């Protein structure tokens, strides 16, 4: 469960970073 | 522009698949 | 309903990729 | 050009089918 | 309506695939 | 050649029958 | 062989559509 | 059920034509 | 080759979706 | 099982198209 | 180049997620 | 703001990973 | 094994994206 | 056990610094 | 740039924490 | 070494957040 | 308050690091 | 050893001083 | 400004303690 | 050498913390 | 009591330093 929550947390950091790239470019 | 929206749609889907993993496991 | 949400999102991404293939090709 | 029109056409139909799965499911 | 729209869309994909066969053959 | 032509005419008819199914349905 | 298999498949589909046209009309 | 059957047949014909496209192309 | 291999892949998915529509509907 | 099989097949197709985009671009 | 490599890697993680979803589901 | 939100999201996952590391080691 | 390989995959994608942000920004 | 305790400690501080940056920025 | 540089530094730490989890797990 | 490598990494990131807080305040 | 909490946090991590140097030295 | 011991003693006094700054501040 | 200078000096000492744990460890 | 300059670094933070209490007290 | 305790601690660190000067010198 704690390794699934880490995956979820990592995933949503990745979505924010992609979101910033599309906002920029 | 089109490339970055494809990028965003991928990570939006990747997130929703990981959300499902956490809900299942 | 979330399994079908995931399915819908993947087909959206598939369509946008193939759209980009036609514009490039 | 013709082959890419076919991929796009097929991609539209696949999207229409998954859209009907989600409405029925 | 959705079912008939999908049948029409598939029918065009099939027609342009056969159009491509005839040109290639 | 003649066989590919018959394939084309068959698909033309199949598409025009589906078109009138949608018009009637 | 596959060309005639396809031709047979189109014919079988054309008949199913026409069959539904008569039921509806 | 009859429109769904018609739909299946069109998909089968469409895949048979793609088999030939792949071989010829 | 790669375009036609993708073309095949769309068809297979479309057929899987339709088989599910037919079973639900 | 069928929802997941179709989900696998969309991802499989989506991965193939992006592979082409990377070669083309 | 780098934008496309990120797109390909997103696709790979999306497929691994789904492969896991298919295994669990 | 968006950069700072990413930083925050990044170090939460990192804290979670180290918590896992601590529990495992 | 597969859950952790997925973790590695998201991690690699995250670093790719931030590498892009740094180059763009 | 002790050296991972130090990892956890630096992780807590790094997070608190980020949180201050985010509130100040 | 100090933000971006900072982000790059945490992304590196995250990756190494992950890489240790997968070797440990 | 791999653990110490991480710990050095966290030290770098913490010091650069502190440097940012000193510059901003 | 937040600034002072961060100083206390840093101080206590430094003490734990020096504790560790004592054991290894 | 005596150099390590003085280091520990220095860190101790530093912590209680910061502990006093936080109570006073 | 004096609290931030003290904060700078704390992290500066902590980094050097870490950097010496890596030689000794 | 580095152990001796850690000693110096700790001493300067110790001095600045006491100077703050004298200023505050 | 806390001011007097910090004073006792500082006295101890300085005495320890004297010891070291006596050993080296």
Image (cartoon, coloured by chain):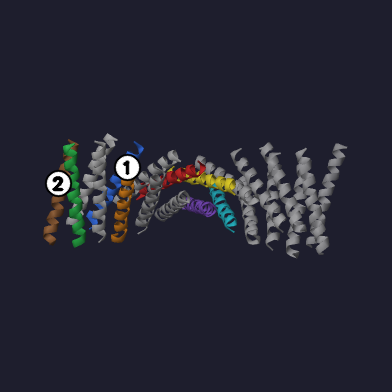
Chain colours: A purple, D orange, F green, G brown, I blue, K red, L cyan, M yellow
* Horizontal side, residue I15 vs residue L14: left or right: left
Q: In which quarter of the image is residue I4?
A: top left
Query: In the image shown, does A22 or D24 lie closer to the viewer?
Result: A22
- Which disc is residue I24 wearing? none
The image shows residue K1 at horizontal and vertical percentages of 50, 41
User: Circle 2: is it few (<14), some (14-19), or many (20+) Cα within 10 Å?
Assistant: some
Residue under disc 1 on the same chain as residue under disc 2: no
Q: Which residue lies under the disc numbered 1?
A: D3
Quick one: quadrant of the N terminus of chain M?
A: top left
Q: Residue at x 48, y 42 (%)?
A: K5
Question: Is residue G17 toward the left or the right of residue K8 in the image?
Answer: left
Instruction: Name the residue beneath numbered marker 2.
Output: G11
- Which mark lies nearer to you, 1 or 2? 1
Left or right of residue M11: residue F17: left
At which x and y percent is residue F6? 16, 42
Nearer to the camera, L5 or F13 = F13
Q: What element carries label 1?
A: helix
Q: Tell me which chain the residue with mark 2 is part of.
A: G
Residue G6 visible in rendering: no
Residue D22 can be seen in this image: yes
Secondary structure category for the residue under label 2? helix
Q: Position of residue M6 (x, y in %)?
A: 45, 45
């Amino acid at each position: 469960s704690k390794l699934l929550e880490l995956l979820r947390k990592l995933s949503e950091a990745l979505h924010k970073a992609i979101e910033l790239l599309e906002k920029w470019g």
